[PDB]
Image (cartoon, rainbow over all chains, first blue to last red; front, side, top):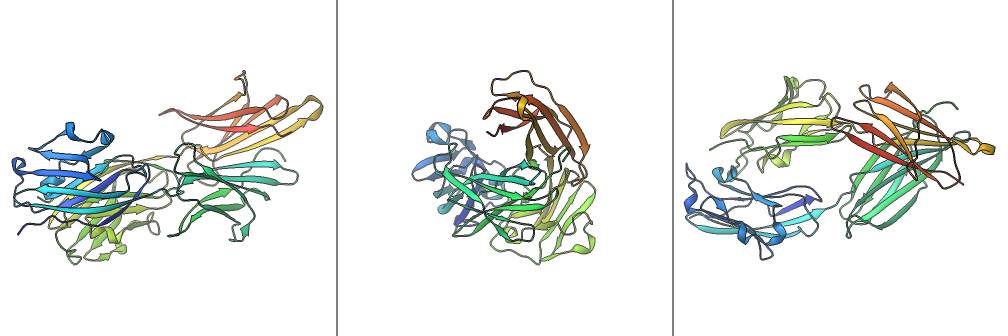
Length: 215
Length: 211
């Protein structure tokens, strides 16, 4: 009878990453464009309007300018694929696709955006090589607030000092930095794990105590 | 009307990281898992092959043994998603995906591994308190070779001794250590910049003189 079909309701997408959502519809042997209406829209704003095999840019809501494109290839296989570059937190929400190829249907893909603590900038300071006390630091930003957990190489937990504030890059994200001061020695290994709950999500960087010139 | 699409002809990915390269293909109504064939192989080596619901190890090369895999849930959706863990310098090259389900197609992904000098370890010593002379030191590993540029809280003309070795821990890396000698007051700011070219990449670290 002809119906528009969605590979999934929900996509959890990665902040500052690129987004690809799909609408599927029947393509008998060949695609011809004259017939086709592809129209994507989220919260009433036009992302994309596909008509006579071109895309009507004049109608694309300003805020989607050159950040949203439509594939041209997967149309050909009965797959309407909306690609959104550099995903923002705002980009979370509900997206309607509307296809009309001899039969109009529509679907509604829900889209969550996550900002995982997954780019961990690390650094090590040998504070006083007589005492062997070092200063290991890990910093990163995501959403929501995360804790840092320090562990030795035998997974014993250690006392750190962690400092959360709002990221100055993005207003909605958090900066998290943690510092361990510990007497250790060349080649010893330590971890800093950025955890965050509901659902839990861990990202941890591996820290190797280096060897520098002359004790 | 069966073609493998690729979302990225190119992946630029960080040494030691986790890489998920993807090949998409038309899935209709249901996942005929008993039908599906996916072959992942890069530049004349075999990574993954997946015959009808089953990952066939027997064949795959040994460099991948415990580190390559196919993301299973994704197949349902039309995503032959190959994942590599602990991405090395060798793992760069040209990746092919052979997918058979309905028709059968193949596309190619280029994979670039950057190993940036970005884990910077640092020392500040007081060599002579009467002269307030300090030794500042900075060390980092990467590829290719880097130079170390030292600058100060006013951009004065500094020079140090840079010492490059092969890395003891990740065999293909350079261990570059640089050492600055200088006189200075407390809470002054210097920086050690490590520098690669091709393309010219710069990573810098800030050193604060303790009181």
